Structure formats: C-alpha cells, structure tokens
Length: 256
Length: 265
Ligand SMILES: NC(=O)c1ccc[n+]([C@@H]2O[C@H](COP(=O)([O-])OP(=O)(O)OC[C@H]3O[C@@H](n4cnc5c(N)ncnc54)[C@H](OP(=O)(O)O)[C@@H]3O)[C@@H](O)[C@H]2O)c1
Ligand SMILES: NC(=O)c1ccc[n+]([C@@H]2O[C@H](COP(=O)([O-])OP(=O)(O)OC[C@H]3O[C@@H](n4cnc5c(N)ncnc54)[C@H](OP(=O)(O)O)[C@@H]3O)[C@@H](O)[C@H]2O)c1
Ligand SMILES: [Ca+2]
Ligand SMILES: [Ca+2]
Ligand SMILES: [Ca+2]
Ligand SMILES: [Ca+2]
Ligand SMILES: [Cl-]
Image (cartoon, rainbow over all chains, first blue to last red; front, side, top):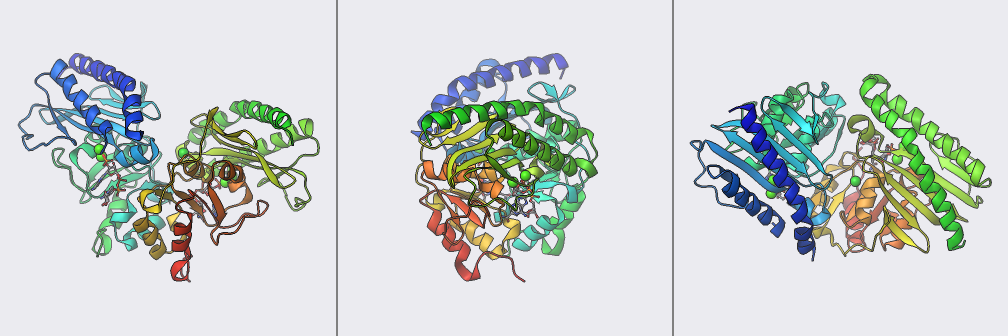
C-alpha cells in the first residue's frame, strides 16, 4: 500500500466521522427519550463502505462475523460504540473504534472520543495523531510510578490487591478504547482487559507499534486480531512487572 | 442575603476563575518539563499561590470574608465566621501530575453557616459547574435538574477501593450496575449531580474536598451525608457519600454491614 492511497482513505474516514457528528445528537436524544446508537452508527459505516470501498469487508460487534477469515484482504474491524454502558448511564466516556487491515497488516486506526471531540488516529508510515497533533512515544513509566486501569470485578481479589500495591494508583474510564489511549498518551502505565473481542482492541495494534507500546496477550505473545485474547496494552517500562503480577500465585482468574 | 447580592458576588467569582488561565496552564506545561521528583512539589506551590491570590481577592472585594484552605493555617476558623469561603485550588493532584486531566477547582461560600454559592471548575474541559441559592445549579450556564431516580442495581458507583476491605468492595461491586473512578472528589461528585453515577464515596475527605457539594446536593435533591447518615460538619469533613436519593440507603447499608467498610487490622 502507498502513502497516497492511505491518505485518500484517511480523508474519507475523517469525513465520515464528521458526518457522524451531524447524526449522533438525534440518536442520543432517541435513546434517552445495546442501543439504536450502536446499531445505527454501524449500519452507516456499512453503507459508507458499500459506497466508497465496495471490496472492503467489516468485522463488527452488531453483526454476525462467521464469514470473516484471514483470507479477507481488505478488512475493517469496528466497535461502533465502545463503552455502551457509559453511553447509556453517563452519555460520556465512550468512543468509536475503527481499524483497517490490508492483507492482515494494520494500516489505519481510529479511536474517536466523540463526547470530548478528540480523534485519535494512526496511519502506517505517517504516525499517530490526536486531532491532527502528532503523538510521540510516552515517557518510561515504571509500575510504581504509574496509574493502572483494569476491571477489578473479573479477577480474584488477591491479585487485584497485588496490582493496587505495586502501582501508583488505580483508575477506570470504562471503555477499552479510551483506557487504551490513556496508555498511549502516557497518562496510564497499562490497561488490561482479560477477555476482549476483536473490536475492543483492533485500533490499538497500530498505535502500539507506532508509539513503542507493548501490546500482548497476558502470556506475552502477539494477539490474533481476528480473535482477540486476554490482553494488555502497556508502557514499555511496566509491561513485564504487570504480567508477572497477573500470572503469579496461580493467576488472575476468579477462584469461585 | 438577596438575589441581587449573590449575582454580584457570582459575577466577580466567574471573572476571577477565568483569570486563572494565567496560572494553571503554566503548571500543566511543567508536568512535562520538570523532573518526576519535583512535580508534586510544584503543584503544592501553585496550590498555595492560587490560594493566596484568592485571599487577596477577598481582602480587596469582600473585606470581612475569610478563607478555609489547605495551604494556610485554619485554627481560628470557627462557626462564628459569618462570611466564609472554603477552597480547594487543585482537587485531584495525582490526576494533574500523572495525567494532566481529571482535576478541578473547588470553591464554596457560606453565609452564617449556610451554603450560598458553590463552584466546581473542571478546568481541562472548561466546564464550570456552579450553584446559586435561589437560582439553581448550572453547567456553563445550562441549568441542571434533579437527576432521574437510580436504584443501586441500575447505577454506576465510584469510590476508592484501596482504602476499604475487599469483602465490602466486592459487595459494592455485586450490588451496583458497574464501577468507575475519575479520581477527583469534585468530579466524581459532579457525576452524581449529573445522574451519571448513583453515588460517590470518600471515606476521609478534608473540608475543601466536599465544600461545594452541599449546595449542589440541596438544589438537585441529592443525599449528602456521613457514612452513618448524619449531616457533615462543613468545617471539619467526615467520611462521606454523595448519592442519588434512590440508592443512598442501600449503599450505606452495604458499607456498614458485617462490621463496616474499614480495612482489617
Ligand atoms: N474481562 C474483563 O477485563 C472485562 C472488562 C469489561 C467487562 N467485562 C464483563 O462485562 C460484563 C458487564 O460489563 P462490565 O462493567 O464488567 O464492562 P463494561 O463496563 O460494560 O465495559 C467495559 C469495557 O469492556 C468491554 N466489554 C463489554 N463486555 C465485555 C466482556 N464480556 N469481556 C470483556 N470486555 C467487555 C466494553 O465494550 P462495549 O462497551 O462495546 O461492550 C468496554 O470497552 C461483566 O459481567 C464482566 O464480566 C469483563
Ligand atoms: N476514600 C478515601 O479515603 C480516599 C480517597 C482518595 C484518596 N485516598 C488515599 O489518599 C492517597 C491519594 O490518592 P491518589 O494517589 O489516588 O490521588 P489523589 O489526587 O491524592 O486523591 C484522590 C481524591 O481524594 C483526595 N485525597 C487526597 N488524599 C486523600 C486522603 N488521604 N483521603 C481522602 N481523599 C484524599 C484528592 O484531593 P487532593 O487532590 O486535593 O489531594 C482527590 O479529590 C492514597 O493513599 C489513597 O489511597 C483515600
Ligand atoms: Ca460496543
Ligand atoms: Ca467494546
Ligand atoms: Ca481535594
Ligand atoms: Ca488540593
Ligand atoms: Cl469528570
């Protein structure tokens, strides 16, 4: 793929996301008085592909994905609303996740923090950006100096306590895409999700590559972008320590 | 106090908070340029400066008005003080230092002990939550209303899990819809005020962490009490909850069951 083609696609995605701005307030007003919001955003993206990129296929949360394989050369993975609980309960702290893979290789990635008007995007060969401003590799963060984010309700409490004690503090935004972007920005040392779907993490691959983040399974391997696996996205300086804590003493799972 | 006087004071405070753009952005810049070792010290220094400047603001506009804040001695501040401001110039210090986000300014005026004006300035998002007795509560001039009823099972809750025993934390997890944490008392409180969270707990706040919230709770029909359901002394602070009216009792029940929420030993 060329830089010229990537920019053309990028230009069309940024325009689509701007059109989304024109539709979403109405969908939100209807929801208020899974949602229609998730399903409509997804359907509109499907129409966008049908119109602009007829060869491209979609793996997304609100459709069946049985026909999506590693043979598909032009693939988008979408979470149309990541943070559905935050959308419904708070109307805040949710995002749109989009990622394009070409012959299996991450080429374009998007995390749109709509409520706060911040577009994180990554373009292979160009870099990562927040609202157009180039992002750089975050400063090194040792676990003891870093805030971490994970779901404490899906782990055994002894392991949750070990994570509390070894880190600087604990926070949770509650949307995978956003908690990940805080790692990307150097605000959090690490974000963990012990059982993500492909759409929860699809954009993050390219961000992790371009910003020198560690993004691995909880066993330290590369993740299958078609399947998802227990995962971490981490600053390079606290990745090993976090994995070590999670896997010590018989591991992080609930004994329950 | 008249609506005319409150507005005059309100207008002054809003203007002063706007002028805070001359201080805060510089501290934020320095969270990048100064070494890790000095960062909390820089924040506490700028906390002290913002506080002193508010002190001077009072001396010049409101000569009898006094100030209760962290960076000054408050030994002489009593229930005898007729005109009292309580201030947290930067609430959410750890978020400022580590994230340069999710921090706020807390300011509250009490007249003869009664909450009259309150401010939570979400500075990174430029969102001024303010409350005025007789007028109501506002976010950037959009008028806030009492939130919908939220039973605990349907609500997101926010608290510091590291300061409670884990059995009680588990009971809070199981009984609520979900768990979130912003990490600044003022902001986690405003999410309760907006109906985004069912409840926020802080088991050991200072007066300045919670001073604004009294008036917001009154005007928006929120329950704001000690963890044993009493009125909180605004001069002293206590273990506290701010909650939607429909999940207040259930949360307190969970916290106080089984010997309470404290850590063991
Ligand atoms: N394994 C984990 O680390 C984890 C993380 C979150 C949630 N959950 C599970 O989700 C159920 C209810 O929601 P919650 O409050 O825990 O999460 P949530 O707060 O509703 O969502 C938190 C984040 O995790 C995603 N998510 C939703 N369901 C998930 C699942 N089953 N496994 C992993 N991630 C998921 C969300 O994606 P969408 O908003 O697009 O759904 C969002 O990005 C729970 O019973 C819990 O087991 C597990
Ligand atoms: N529920 C609680 O008792 C509670 C709540 C928060 C923090 N803490 C403890 O205090 C320390 C600071 O927390 P952090 O590193 O997450 O971030 P933080 O920015 O220091 O504290 C988070 C929030 O609680 C306030 N705070 C600071 N020290 C506190 C204390 N001892 N008790 C209650 N509230 C406090 C903060 O106000 P300022 O930014 O003005 O300090 C902010 O509103 C840790 O040891 C933490 O576990 C306890
Ligand atoms: Ca979703
Ligand atoms: Ca998701
Ligand atoms: Ca505070
Ligand atoms: Ca403070
Ligand atoms: Cl907030």
